[PDB]
Length: 145
Length: 145
Ligand code: HEM
Ligand code: HEM
Image (tube, rainbow over all chains, first blue to last red; front, side, top):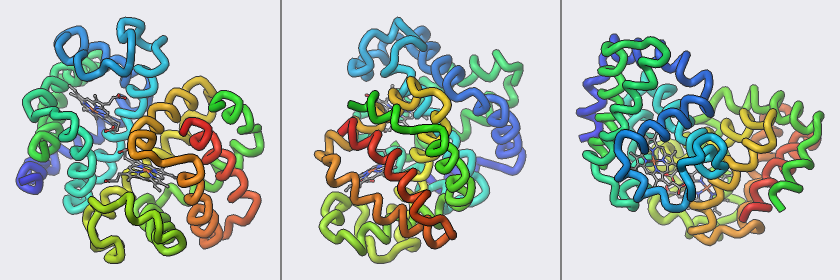
């Protein structure tokens, strides 16, 4: 199942993922926080899953939110680093899904991250072509939920 | 406290952490699995916390163990990257501790990783000086458990 989704990661898709990550991943704190705050802005209901982070309206200044945001970026770093070996990509994605499954986060709920990603890519001038590539990566994770 | 522990990361300790990580972090899959297998070999009592992984003796062939081992290395990568900013290191460490606290992993339990780290370091020609630097980093996490 996850393997089949991974099959959509064509040579061109992996190339766009790597090229865009080279920029996005260069500022994990800044972009990580941008993703989370955008998610909360566009889909307020997702805040229900982050009660532990406290006052998320504080953004970057909120230590717990900042800690979560930076950490989230290292999961993507992990995924990006395993793109050339489907076997490693798959085992890393299934390992990542475990805690999210426990939190009862469905594939549909997880898919809400596509908008924030598209918006962050755009802020760095990466168009639809790149947003589509990332949608495919998110789809691999969705296959594991 | 975690804030006092973070202050123990002096200039040379940070430098030795970076220099050794440059090598160790080069092969996350290889060294990550070596780290876990050494832990299970030297402290069989810890295997109980990893029931979900299945037959841990299979090493690299165990997909779940490989997935976990690779992922563990990105938490260390995270810590190393935050060495420049104590405030970020602390929020990233507390974030990391949440799940380990939920699993009831105590500071004493966590410290058992010092043995495996020292051995992997040694296998790459990094002696006591480096093992001690890493123990200082591990102590920051212990302070948060
Ligand atoms: C590209 C998307 C995402 C990435 C890379 C990501 C990454 C992570 C990582 C690495 C962690 C820490 C390890 C763990 O506990 O699992 C985590 C925690 C968490 N994630 Fe995800 N996640 C993503 C999307 C989501 C979404 C869409 C939701 C909810 C709507 C979600 C909810 C959670 C929650 C509630 C936590 C715990 C937060 C805390 O209390 O510190 N994640 N995620
Ligand atoms: C260098 C030290 C260590 C690092 C960097 C580390 C890293 C991680 C990471 C990144 C995860 C995934 C996120 C999460 O679920 O929290 C994790 C999971 C876990 N860790 Fe730690 N950990 C370390 C030591 C330990 C020790 C010493 C124990 C137990 C004695 C432990 C027990 C666990 C368990 C049971 C899981 C879940 C495994 C699974 O079911 O997939 N960790 N750890």
